[PDB]
Image (cartoon, rainbow over all chains, first blue to last red; front, side):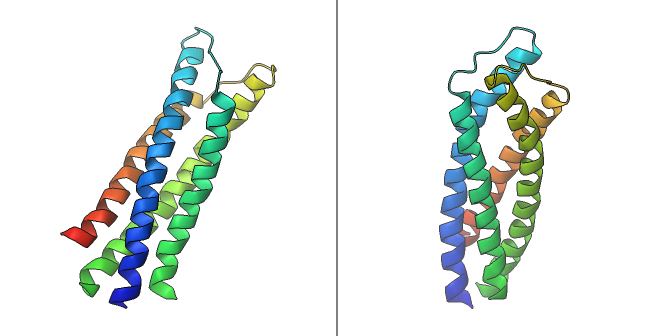
Length: 75
Length: 75
């Protein structure tokens, strides 16, 4: 019980901290361009496709972290 | 040790599962419009400001989950 769980928590907390940093950077780029478009200023979409790909991967990786944490209590 | 930790894991796994579902829905809207704009088809930005606000809150909430998990091993 105690041994198996803490390892799961450490590894996933680290993965989560990394994924949050990645989401933050990529979404900063996306939110800035969307602010411009909604401001009627047009938008520079340079690099945005790549940021979107990165966020899609991060969401899936976050889902894996959630699954790992939940599984650690069950089996 | 064992008692304090599992509660942290359960509550945060639940919060994480909820936040991932929220991020997924909001980002589906954002990625669809960005795909359109990069496709040269223009973009319908209806509702997008609100999705951006929601993702900003979810990122901050994810950071709180990461902090809680890490703190549970230390103090």
